[PDB]
Amino acid sequence: PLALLPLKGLREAAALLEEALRQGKRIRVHGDYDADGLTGTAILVRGLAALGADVHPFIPHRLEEGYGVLMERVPEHLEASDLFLTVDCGITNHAELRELLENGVEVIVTDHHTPGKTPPPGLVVHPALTPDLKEKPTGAGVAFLLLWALHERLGLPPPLEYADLAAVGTIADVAPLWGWNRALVKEGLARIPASSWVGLRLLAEAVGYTGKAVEVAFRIAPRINAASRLGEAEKALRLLLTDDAAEAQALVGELHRLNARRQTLEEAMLRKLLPQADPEAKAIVLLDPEGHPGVMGIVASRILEATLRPVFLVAQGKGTVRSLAPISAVEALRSAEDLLLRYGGHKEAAGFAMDEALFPAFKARVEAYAARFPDPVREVALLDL
Ligand SMILES: [Mn+2]
């Protein structure tokens, strides 16, 4: 049964929010552009506003600026808020220490992604930093809990009215769905048909939602994620806020387009690139001069799943990477570094930019790099698929 799951930080957070409410502070909710993040952002933005707060959302542009809090827009975050609230990001954006410094903007970091060495500055609400807890809530999950807590003090009923959104974000992030997640999802799914948010009702209707969870995961979530991938996140967020049946359906249709267009672009890129793969290579290094970068990542993962080799795709001047077993995406990019303009990431995934003119040289460098190291087949349980 749904219960306000512990979580080390909620009390302090709720405190800070109520404080903001009374003082009429400007609250900027900085979420992610994926379904979990957008959905979570919606919860806090409506919830707070519902309690007469001064809230406005802020979503990054997946294609121009990356994920998380962007340092370049920090100055802009300052002039716009008194309380900076993070939704599905933050824990590794330590340079928002400038938030607390530069001016006195209180920072509340909500997240669920793998934490770094040290937590980031500010009041943190992360499930992995809660002592003896193994519930695994998602970004939208944490926001829901956060809205719940704020409801506790102030003395208002639990925010069940918001479980649907929270449910969409959870399934979207394919959480275990075995812990408290189950109660949230089950409760959420049930409230979708005729929920309190037209955008979500109409959408659920459009995709013929019956009540199944697979329907949220395979028809609803894709539609919401499709927007950011084509530089149209806002459209998705607005759908989730709006509550104007008119504007709603218009948006539902705009998401239909976006989703279809994303799918067509993946299929198109895939059938152009897959044949060029070839598992005989220590690393797959392909170049689709005219490929939409907002879709390469997906294609890279599928090419990997198919070849069990590191994949390096470059389209326009951008590049993504997906590798496994020995080879590390970033470290591969370490060499050839000179050939790049920028680059960053981790072991399994990484990104970068470069002048396509150096592609041949880059391909040979990365190939040679993976030439060292064993063959990934001597590691994966193949359930890797
Ligand atoms: Mn998430």
Image: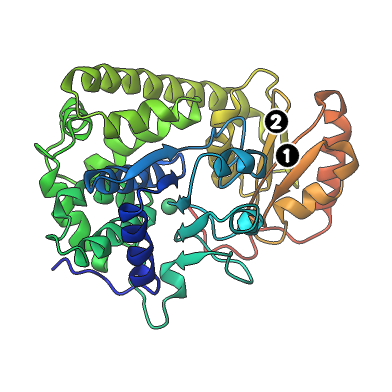
Q: Is residue 7 above or below residue 74?
A: below
Q: Residue at x 69, y 35 (%)?
A: 319
Q: Is residue 79 left or right of residue 176?
A: right
Name the residue carrying label 1: 352
Front position in the image: 105 or 382: 105
Q: Is residue 291 above or below residue 280?
A: above
The answer to whether residue 252 is left or right of residue 350 is left
- The answer to whether the residue labelled 1 contacts the one labelled 2, judged by CB atoms less than 8 Å apart, is yes
Q: Residue at x 50, y 58 (%)?
A: 107
Q: Residue at x 49, y 45 (%)?
A: 81
Q: Does the image show residue 383?
A: no
Residue type, mark 1 in image: Phe
What's the amino acid at mark 2? Answer: Lys
Q: Give whichever of 72, 338 is nearer the camera.
A: 72
Task: Indicate the position of residue 254 as horizontal and vertical percent values.
Answer: 33, 18
**Numbered circles on residues, count:** 2
The quarter of the image holding the N terminus is bottom left
What mark, if any, has residue 318 been given in the picture?
2
Disc 1, SS: strand
What's the residue at 56%, 40% (across, down)?
A: 79
Residue 293 is tagged as: none
| Alpha carbon separation for disc pair 1 and 2 | 6 Å
- The residue most toward the bottom is 132
Label 2 secondary element: strand
Image position, residue 155 (x, y; %): 15, 64
Mark 2 CB lies closer than 8 A to ligand 1: no
Residue 338 figure quarter = top right
